[PDB]
Image (tube, rainbow, N blue to C red):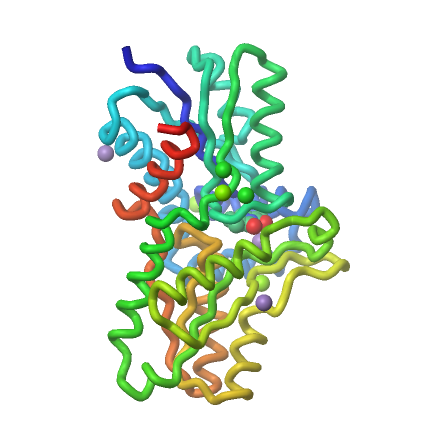
Length: 309
Ligand SMILES: *Cc1c(C)c(=O)n2c(=O)c(C)c(C)n12
Ligand SMILES: [Cl-]
Ligand SMILES: [Cl-]
Ligand SMILES: [Mg+2]
Ligand SMILES: [Mg+2]
Ligand SMILES: [Mg+2]
Ligand SMILES: [Mn+2]
Ligand SMILES: [Mn+2]
Ligand SMILES: [Mn+2]
């Protein structure tokens, strides 16, 4: 007498091989194919971070581990996971169509991004519900945010504590914690979008639980459009704080991201590292959640809380 439920896990997506770069970035750029020089630059960046194929495996592993863990920790519901991506197949609509074809009538969705925004999360949930409505006979209840789930806060708190415990004593007393997420166009403010407030609260909760008194909030990985995006960018923030107070170590927590992808392995571990190397400071960036059991249990709790169980 276990009830059957779909578990729709949504994410941005990643190329599966080098020859996917063109079509992935064309989709991100709203139909504008990157010029040859940019295509070559992107290939070089992926080669520099160790290759493309490991990156797509992570979302698959997160969805699989989440399904199995959810089915182990309670006895009322049997979940089946379906992956729906924004920028490459399987797309969100493909996942909903597959759920419908398989006989799913009830689903719960979650986006692998802990902060709500009108640009990403709300768009993903709207797409999923609209496909379900067009097909009929299937309903979806959607997680909207989960940055404040205690288990997730604790993941990052314990990683930050481990990092501060490892540094030399002079660094430990003169370090700066930078907490960041993916930048979005500033115009989201016109809708009252809580995304910036939620990033600031994540930073408060992590710094507080870790006992870190000196921290700052920044943004990273902005796209390219004429209208402004949320700032300051982590590169400028790092340099400005160093000019202000001479910090000897910077610790980066990209809380908006859940996996080892280009926006962390390159935009932090390279682009921020260039700045810290130039100023003479040490660089630290603790492990991303990926598919680790502590993170999977946090996500399972988010899902069961959403269902009132
Ligand atoms: C992959 C991706 C894009 C294109 C984007 O705008 N964002 C976000 O805001 C997040 C959190 C992720 C992932 N992505
Ligand atoms: Cl929610
Ligand atoms: Cl929310
Ligand atoms: Mg090849
Ligand atoms: Mg909430
Ligand atoms: Mg960039
Ligand atoms: Mn397993
Ligand atoms: Mn601020
Ligand atoms: Mn981006």
